Image 1 (cartoon, rainbow, N blue to C red):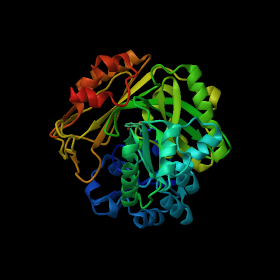
Image 2: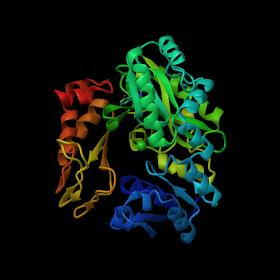
Image 3: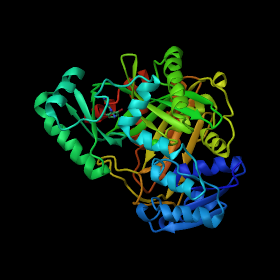
Length: 446
Ligand SMILES: Nc1ncc2cc(-c3c(Br)cccc3Br)c(N)nc2n1
Ligand SMILES: [Cl-]
């Protein structure tokens, strides 16, 4: 078991990682910006290192400072959490080069999944169903590009290979817009990622966003841990996630899960991972893979009983997976509401000092947050300050518990999305289940 790790993150996920470390007897090093001195996990950590000023570029994205903190404390590993450097292959490369364990896959694997074109090619080869597409980068020959779009059939979507999570993409519905749409996506990709490579896919009009959780060790074991429905979103930002996905049969789960686990074996995957799919008309279509542990990981934990962060740490230490596939069983239902410090009218981050705080409790209620009474939410980082996760024997009980929990949650002094989350729980279409990726924005528009 790893002696000491650097938690290379902040907020709720850093606290999540800290708890996992404490359970396994792993010493904690909390690296933090000067604005994050009073973070809950920082105050609970065995050792603390201030790695720079408030802006992320000089703290949480500061590669030399994070590695130096690992060096000075005698830490053996670095957990990147999600966001920041978690998908940075060069960082993972430098970490291993410096002699520390990167809690994640090999840098080569991160690089592969960050290249959406090569990732799709690897998945298609492995037998994972993908979106009908160009199967390769688009060139400058517009006669060829029109032929590809005709073969696929309009509408199509142009996507940046260096993009992801809905960054750098646009829908094309006819030949007249194809040239300009390709050029613009290319230009945006060059400006944002220093990679102008773009590809084409059949545009699915009303899919659900369904993703498969995987775990793979260094002993050759690779398992799938059911799916998550992440369709309740606004402008490429998840709002509510749930597990399992409504309407997904054990047969479908088995079908797509086995294909994801087989892909892990083929590519030599290691650690936690997420296969993102579009789900439409009872069919799965792979779009991208995430190599990090994700925001919405707790819903998977509730329905399987598997502590995913602890599995990450065990894998990194050289231990096999604590569970086999036949030991993985979907039981009950979990819903996650992301709690954001945001203005209800603009959806812009709303930082400030929390004057009164109270967390919900009870059977099946899980609260994941660093916030406390007197805590100031800084303006420099993401708006998400907490996660409320509710579990039940069925979906209806999970939703009922969420409604009760949201009503107990008090966060005064700052503006939050608690009222919005309550509106979503009370939404008849959500209560029926199976709403698509576009539902929330349509609801808010009406
Ligand atoms: N080929 C397609 N067809 C449809 C889609 C849809 C999404 C999507 C998703 Br999965 C979530 C929110 C918005 C959007 Br535009 C996406 N990220 N990628 C897609 N690729
Ligand atoms: Cl994430």
